[PDB]
Amino acid sequence: SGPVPSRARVYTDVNTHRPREYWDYESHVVEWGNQDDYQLVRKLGRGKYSEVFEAINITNNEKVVVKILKPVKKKKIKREIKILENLRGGPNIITLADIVKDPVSRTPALVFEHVNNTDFKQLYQTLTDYDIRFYMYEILKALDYCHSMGIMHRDVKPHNVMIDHEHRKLRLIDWGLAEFYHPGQEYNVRVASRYFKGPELLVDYQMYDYSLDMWSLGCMLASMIFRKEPFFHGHDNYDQLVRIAKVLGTEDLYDYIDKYNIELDPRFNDILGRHSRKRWERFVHSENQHLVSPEALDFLDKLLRYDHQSRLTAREAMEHPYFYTVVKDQAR
Ligand SMILES: O=C(CCC(=O)NCCc1ccc(Cl)c(Cl)c1)NCCCCn1cnc2c(Br)c(Br)c(Br)c(Br)c21
Ligand SMILES: NCCc1ccc(Cl)c(Cl)c1
């Protein structure tokens, strides 16, 4: 007997009710702009999948960001484009402005709205309790939206959160790993950065859903309030689950494994050991106590659960007491 199937608790059938063109990205036809509308100004960074530039649209003098893609399978470019187009205009989702073909490498380039990013070295030095609650709530808006639109981001981490702090403006970026959720579909578990991988990825449980993003969000929250980056600091994918188990305990892990009849890689036998579930107080000290509260710890505990089905949804997270003062402030 194999693993027990699983279904998302919410937004389970949203893609089923769509025309197939919404989610059948392999059949998407790309609408191309004119690369001659743009001039590159300077390089902002480079990754395994792209090089990123600041640019100017010389037809309207607008600043934009240009992501020149490295060679990748055409269906993965179509996937990112289709998801960006489907989510465009949603709260705190980066806006795809144009798609052009780089004359040099003949590769596609995505053109995004510019965000005046805040120097985060200063941001983290003066970060307040209220700042963290406010921006977490802004991220939850983007996640509830994309989940409600049938999409898992699958790469939630601080690097993919742009913040213009002067204007309290936040954007969730890099949708190149995002996928459409379909009930019963088995997904690739080699997604997300190591430190933010959910337990379902680490034990190779492929029938996962939106709740994967909620684990990653809990990892980000823990690093913020405890000022410990990364929070779960594994040496490799195997050790990453050991680091989680030393905090969440091994009992709930084996309860999770048994519930879904997951066949655990035999490497884990001699490294997981036996660990109690720790109390969050052991990460609190004089340098982070101003960011930690009973509300923050209650919220954090309800995100970081082995069982993906028992994690808060994005909308449930937004209703947590941790956000009460943010919610009433936004009512104005
Ligand atoms: O520096 C970062 C962000 C690092 C960071 O700590 N965040 C804030 C994290 C955070 C999250 C939650 C909370 Cl609660 C709080 Cl408090 C803080 N990531 C590098 C991006 C590399 C350059 N890069 C790539 N793609 C880009 C796009 Br697309 C645009 Br548009 C723009 Br602009 C740029 Br620059 C782009
Ligand atoms: N049109 C020449 C400048 C240029 C080169 C490459 C790209 Cl991808 C862009 Cl948008 C603009």
Image: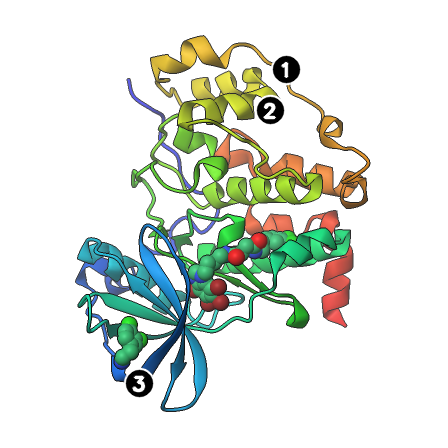
**Alpha-carbon distance for marks 2 and 1?**
7 Å
Tag 1 residue: 276
Does any portion of residue 26 appear in the rendered image?
Answer: yes
Counting residues from the start of the chain, the first of labels 3 and 1 encountered is: 3
Tag 2 residue: 248
Q: Residue at x 52, y 10 (%)?
A: 273
Q: Amino acid at mark 2?
A: Leu
Q: Residue at x 71, y 30 (%)?
A: 283
**Alpha-carbon distance for marks 3 and 1?**
59 Å
Label 1: few (<14), some (14–19) or many (≥20) C-alpha neighbours in 10 Å: few
| Residue farthest along the bottom direction in this orientation | 59
Q: Which mark is residue 310?
A: none
**Mark 3: C-beta under 8 Å from nearest atom of ligand 2:** yes
Q: Which quarter of the rendered picture does the C terminus lie within?
A: bottom right
How many numbered marks appear? 3
Tag 3 residue: 37
